[PDB]
Every structure is written in C-alpha cells, then in structure tokens.
Image (cartoon, rainbow, N blue to C red; front, side, top):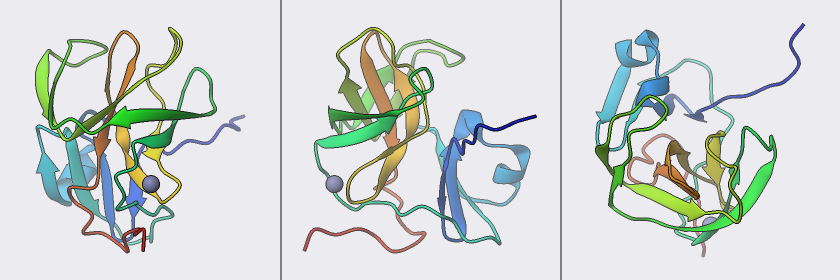
Length: 150
Ligand SMILES: [Zn+2]
C-alpha cells in the first residue's frame, strides 16, 4: 500500500517539537512547552528522536518541499515577529521567531523541517507569495545536544 515516508516535525531526544496546527491531542496531553506566537510546542516521548537541532544562525540552509518532494537550498533571514497572512487554515496573525526564504519560482508552500549543514533549524510555519516561513527551534533547544561552529 503506502511507501512514501514523512515526519512533518522535529523529534529531539525525549522532547518532540511540532507545529501547533500539526500537534495532536497526545502532544498537548504530555506537552511541556508551547509558544502561540511560534505556533510550536514541545511534548515528551519514550522513544529517542532521530534529529539534531543546529545552534547556528547561518543565513543559508536547505528546506524540504512537498510539491518538489526534494530538498531546496535557500537563503533566509530570522525575523522576530512576522505577520502571517490568512492562508491554508490560519488567520492573519502575528508569529514570533520565524525565518523566511524567498525562492526563485512560484511553487513552494509547505514541506517538512528546515535543516542546516550544522543541524535542524525549524519547521514549516507560514508561507507567502514566494517566501518560506519557518519556525526556528533555536529558542528552545532544551531537548538534546546542540550544534556549534567551534
Ligand atoms: Zn548552519
């Protein structure tokens, strides 16, 4: 039957951070932290994760695309508060700690998680007419080892 695999979230050790609109009743049931402005929350799990978050701030990284189903290297900025337009299933609200990346085409809306050569940055937050909004996990790394530059 099935074949394609996907996580749609970031599993870190005994803490799993996923998008609020993507979290399940179980995520909130055992949720330790949750930032509305970041639309992200952290829940505890028994099974160790398989992802390593990067503690870097490189302006260049690679994001995953659902349409392309491939990894896309793109440069982005880490704007604090970004007003997300009412799209998909979210109302025009303010989001904190979101990184945006302007692609070079029309496609590119959602995907998975934004990872850098050092580690994991964040998950797909909101998107624009040609930009990629990602919720950085650099504001709540308390989950596992962090990536450094030294
Ligand atoms: Zn990096």
